[PDB]
Amino acid sequence: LPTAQEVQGLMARYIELVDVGDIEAIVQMYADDATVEDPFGQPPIHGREQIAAFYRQGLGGGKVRACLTGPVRASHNGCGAMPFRIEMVWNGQPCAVDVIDVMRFDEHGRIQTMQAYWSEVNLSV
Image (cartoon, rainbow, N blue to C red):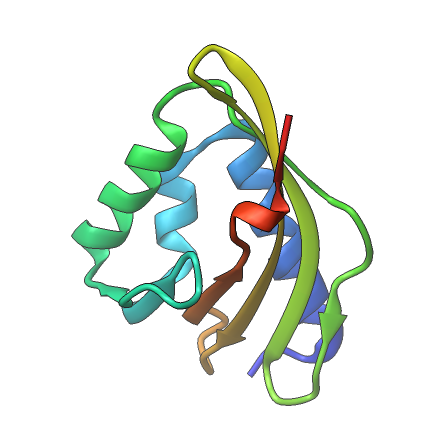
């Protein structure tokens, strides 16, 4: 189980990978039986191929940017939460979404569960 400091690192690393848009690197951060709920409230997606397809859909557009908007909050049980902003292009319009990701890591330092909190109230132009 990642220490709190290690959770901070992994979670910041995740945002960095999203920001440069390395899909393969993002998918490698996940455990084989990981789940992704994004946005939280929608049914979880499971399976490495499914998670790759998710990130391909989301980031494969090319110009998606992401950055922490505050420090990573980390627990002593391998979990953490972080606020960030995603910038992307919607219908040729620049737009942004404010998100919080909650993650649990497994004993191998891999993401076991990802929950992304956001909705239309968090979307702007």
